[PDB]
Amino acid sequence: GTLIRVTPEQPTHAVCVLGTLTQLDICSSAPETSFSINASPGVVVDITWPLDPGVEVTLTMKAASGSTGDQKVQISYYGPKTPPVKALLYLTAVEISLCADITRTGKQRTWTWGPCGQGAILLVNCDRDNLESSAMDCEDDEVLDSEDLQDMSLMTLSTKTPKDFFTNHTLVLHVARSEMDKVRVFQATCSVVLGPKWPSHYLMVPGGKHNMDFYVEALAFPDTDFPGLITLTISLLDTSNLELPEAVVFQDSVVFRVAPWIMTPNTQPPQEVYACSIFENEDFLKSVTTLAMKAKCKLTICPEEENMDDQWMQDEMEIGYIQAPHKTLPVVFDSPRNRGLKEFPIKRVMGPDFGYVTRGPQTGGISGLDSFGNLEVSPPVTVRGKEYPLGRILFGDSCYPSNDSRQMHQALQDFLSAQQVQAPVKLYSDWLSVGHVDEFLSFVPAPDRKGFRLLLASPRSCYKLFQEQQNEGHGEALLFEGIKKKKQQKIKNILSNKTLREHNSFVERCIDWNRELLKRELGLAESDIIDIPQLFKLKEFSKAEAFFPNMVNMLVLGKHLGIPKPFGPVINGRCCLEEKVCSLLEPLGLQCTFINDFFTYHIRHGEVHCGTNVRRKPFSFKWWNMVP
Amino acid sequence: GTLIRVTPEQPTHAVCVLGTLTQLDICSSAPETSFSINASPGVVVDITWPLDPGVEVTLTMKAASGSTGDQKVQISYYGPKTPPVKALLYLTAVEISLCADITRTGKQRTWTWGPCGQGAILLVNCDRDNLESSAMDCEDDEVLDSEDLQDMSLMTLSTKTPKDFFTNHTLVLHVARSEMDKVRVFQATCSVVLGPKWPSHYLMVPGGKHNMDFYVEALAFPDTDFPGLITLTISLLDTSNLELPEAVVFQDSVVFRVAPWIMTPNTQPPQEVYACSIFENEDFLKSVTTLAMKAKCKLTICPEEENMDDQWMQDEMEIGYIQAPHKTLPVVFDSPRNRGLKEFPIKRVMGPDFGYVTRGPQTGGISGLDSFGNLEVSPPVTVRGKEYPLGRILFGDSCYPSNDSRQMHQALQDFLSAQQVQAPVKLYSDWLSVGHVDEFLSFVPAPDRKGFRLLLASPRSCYKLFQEQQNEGHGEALLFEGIKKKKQQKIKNILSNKTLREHNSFVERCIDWNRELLKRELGLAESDIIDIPQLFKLKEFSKAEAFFPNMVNMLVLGKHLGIPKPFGPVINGRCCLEEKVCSLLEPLGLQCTFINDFFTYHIRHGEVHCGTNVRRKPFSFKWWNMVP
Ligand SMILES: *CC(=N)NCCC[C@H](NC(=O)c1ccccc1C(=O)O)C(N)=O
Ligand SMILES: *CC(=N)NCCC[C@H](NC(=O)c1ccccc1C(=O)O)C(N)=O
Ligand SMILES: [Ca+2]
Ligand SMILES: [Ca+2]
Ligand SMILES: [Ca+2]
Ligand SMILES: [Ca+2]
Ligand SMILES: [Ca+2]
Ligand SMILES: [Ca+2]
Ligand SMILES: [Ca+2]
Ligand SMILES: [Ca+2]
Ligand SMILES: [Ca+2]
Ligand SMILES: [Ca+2]
């Protein structure tokens, strides 16, 4: 909006940017009734008229000016006995449009969510396209590679003005000091114009028709102190007066939203599997390699030289992605646990079209619940009307905070919440010794229902299984048959052990709490849930450990499952625990491969899921079309 | 929600909290068809029934139990040729309700805005009821005075259980580690139970009927890293097993929202006026004292001994308020400018039922735009449908950030935005030497329209005024008549000064920018706006100063106005600038008192508004009934 004050004493000169509201104040400086307006064909004047303040006179140009003051407006002040007196207004029309991908196709003043919403997307340039280097591309203020531009968002300044227009006018591009530390802008028309150091920059633009392309990168993900919006503004400045300060004639903006980090649940097709080569574990890696081949996945193994004897590939990282209309890339969330695998995410997971992010204190102040076996996501779900088309992040906690209770670090929690798009749900995992949600739950694909099943570890199911076997006459059947370096236990002695039953009743109560929590927060019914037979035992600090290899802690590669080999009671030639799991999962079209991880992973308090990790296909559903 | 697993082998014992959903799993542990349910009169069982997993059996008690397991449920498993087998369930019903003022009358699981919304209000205990002390009441972990409890929110735990119920159960009250630094909870049943040090506390509660009152205080206002919500939770713990860990049976919560700091516009009735006694300024203080008496306001004067020669009472502080259903108190926002008045807000503005808050760096890194003459609020307005019933905060900025541009510190900006309820609007004030929005705008009450008028300083109006006087033959009339220690200037020489006209055209352009900005963001029309004749001059760095005493910079005490005496051209016995202002404002029923502030305030680049401050009545509209 602009109000031009015309005067019969002196002629007025003004600039009009196309698509803006221009109005005239005719009365204030009028002499002493009545007035009439006559304008050149290029000016459309909407409103033989009385001199009354309330009469709105609005002007709109249709095209940009060829020369300065080429459009005219003439206001004639007259009266009953007064010859007309003329006030002149010389107009110069110009086009000044700051353009971006606001429709989100790859080509209001606010950013709005949803399929009918508007607002451009910005990716955090957190990968490393630069060949042979250490830092992320966004850590410096240069565009080192042409491929790097593919990660950036295009913004174009289009101008149509007279040839001499920028003799007396100047354009300045700017971003608030609040947001300058989170964005960098390069001029292509690459050299930096806006960034952490510079909040504003004078643009060198020639008169006539011109197009100036910019490439923009984000430097920070959404977080506690960053909602995730970045506004870039162009200002047209009148610099006609050599002694007076510059005056702003017109401002226009584009609002960018920084793309969130997004996780992928087990129901998303796998693309790449990760694992470690360690102590005598060659046969474990054979089984995983075969499983990866069956699921047609790329396979990456971290060797002992880089491992520092850290076998827990699940725990150091989580592989997610970031997504814009023009570019989608995987992004590794590096856990602050910083064990032997500390460098793996940095050295050769991060790279060309593979982003990096980390959170929390790096030198200490961490717990086991910061290991990313404690970080998972559900498949897409709808909870009492509200859609979660990218699912819901799940992470483990205590039921309330005490001196002995553990939590995932608040910096990690806050980051996950600030991504917004997978609204995190706190589960109860602190009753476990290790304390990870993957120790009692998993998700698998399914051909019916909601496209999945929630698997939960279940003492109830195992007691039921073992009692059925004893009822059928297999009381002597031995748990841990096949393991020569351990004392076997008969089904009858397992069932008669009152303390083991007490322990498992408490664990059942802990899992049941999570069951109902998941049913409420994911909108699940019992028909979505399958119980996996699993016994537990309480050890140090009354914390739960797996009695036999924790079968729910499995590697899910599409319909191919890598399940820990339980070494259960062999009845009719086969482990009754394997047969039970097969009977539950084979009807869903899942293929169960039981992997021997006993002396390699199990005895060190983890299983197949703990020893591996997976990169999965990003969702086809675009995050910005959600309404969180 | 809770799912109790019944069994014919062993009887089940369980607790049921009234108002919770309890269901039975009858099939999982059923022997081998059909089943029937019979329960005691206290148990209402909703659902001669087949053993099919999908059959929902839900139980609800009507009243709390007198003794442990006093309610019974009997599930009879039978078949075509099978005598019935019984599974027993012993139920204990208890009431556990955590109550607060969720309806906001002073007496879902989320906090919702609006008159049909729910959620309790928490005040930040930032005043000082403790007689003879320095710190705010919330800085320690004790309730020192009985009056202090009036600022706190009441929360009551009501329980109805068997007499021996807490032999095997325990209640724990807790708040997340995330929020514990922002709240403190005292047990009245005063001693602290939750706070910055303690996130949880075991409650000592006797069996039977009991009521436990708590008093809660907030320790922080809403801010960048604090949305303003605090959740307090009660957990019922099963401690029946001396070797097993405690197990959670039931959790319930109350969500508090911390009350925002709220400003009061000039259209709110004044209650107390502030000023300084300094160099020869006794006559200035007489005029203000008389004005305060006319508006029936309390008067507070900071003496020279405390001033340290700092006369700018407007700049060091802003007097707002905080509001809850049970308590409303004024709260002083202390500016970080920390000039001679540094201590005034701390020493005897803060006190009994007078809160304190401050923001920004205290030892340096500040600008003139952090002075609270640059912090104002509009009256209530509705902008294209959206109501702002508490108005909109206004503060001055530049049009874009450059090396020479100034801004209010981001910490102050962020705080104001985080209060949410008066959605701040950035204006353009940096063109002024001092740089304050009060230098070019004010608001006054009005009996018609929206209940107010926006006053804007206007060179246009003054040139028009002076030209009319010259046309009527008063060209010799002297600006600064009555001032013996300054050179007078004739109306004809003022009008013929081309450089003065150039300067004022630029200033007019700066004010016009704000005019349209205010029209858009406050929904104003021209009929809401009155121009006040005012000339300006550019000095150091081409920054604007008032040519004669800045009349818009006035003290607004209801219908009584304290306007700077312009000492304009005397025509027909009276200053033509005074007569013009009177002609504009007297029709609104405003009383104009022109105060001589020339050699006291004006020559030091400020006026009557700058030298004073006002505490005003809080809005009757309750902030929580807004939908921001
Ligand atoms: C399911 C899952 N993510 N598990 C990870 C938990 C296992 C590791 N284990 C160890 O650190 C450990 C335990 C005993 C002996 C050796 C080792 C080891 O050095 O790997 C954990 N607790 O984090
Ligand atoms: C309208 C308003 N809030 N004005 C405050 C601006 C005036 C003060 N003035 C001074 O600091 C000053 C200027 C010249 C000579 C002495 C003094 C003084 O020490 O008070 C400001 N610029 O903050
Ligand atoms: Ca770069
Ligand atoms: Ca890149
Ligand atoms: Ca790490
Ligand atoms: Ca790339
Ligand atoms: Ca994980
Ligand atoms: Ca206290
Ligand atoms: Ca108090
Ligand atoms: Ca201060
Ligand atoms: Ca009080
Ligand atoms: Ca103020």
Image (tube, coloured by chain):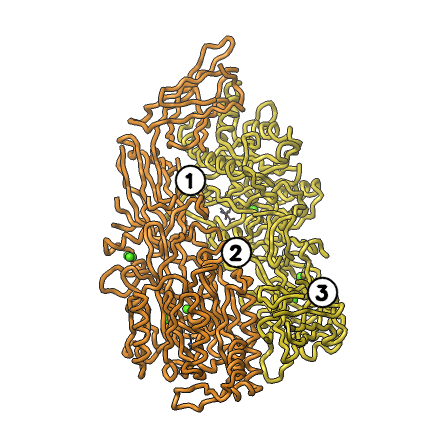
Chain colours: A orange, B yellow
Q: Is residue A249 above or below residue A196?
A: above
Query: Label 1 is found on which chain of the structure?
Result: B
Instruction: Specify the amino acid type for callout 1.
Output: Lys
For residue A133, which quarter of the picture?
bottom left
Residue B434 appears in the figure? no
**Residue at 38% of width from left, 54% of height from top?**
A620
Total marks drawn? 3
The answer to whether the residue bearing label 1 lies less than 8 angstroms from the nearest atom of ligand 2 is no
Q: Residue A495 appears at what percent x and percent y?
A: 54, 85
Q: Which residue is mark 1?
A: B539
Q: Which residue is mark 3?
A: B44
- Kindly identify which numbered label has been placed on residue B180: none
Residue B455 appears in the figure? yes
For residue B340, which quarter of the picture?
bottom right
Q: Residue B538 appears at what percent x and percent y?
A: 43, 38
Q: Earlier in the sequence, mark 3 or mark 1?
A: 3
Q: Residue A191 appears at what percent x and percent y?
A: 26, 50
